[PDB]
Amino acid sequence: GSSGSSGSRKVFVGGLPPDIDEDEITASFRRFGPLVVDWPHKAESKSYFPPKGYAFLLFQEESSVQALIDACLEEDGKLYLCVSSPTIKDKPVQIRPWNLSDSDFVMDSGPSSG
Image (spheres, rainbow, N blue to C red):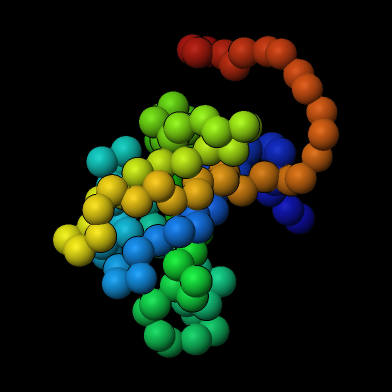
């Protein structure tokens, strides 16, 4: 199987500080809600230093995801969020909610309650 359009909570982050760690990344995105950090080189490898500063965030709940977007600034369609670090100042990381690359527009709303 595969989750891209259905509703993938995962979130792509690019631009993380050059002196940041796992936990740090979490706290930066903890406020929104319980989440977990995992980069393409987290399991296979050991080093806990997200290459070229980048990793994937898997928020326990989907809702949180939405909240993120809202906070994430809008620059020509692309989204960007600010993440302050003990060393580096509020850095505008590239937050791109993992999704199936496709070109299709659709207007609709979800069922608040049921």
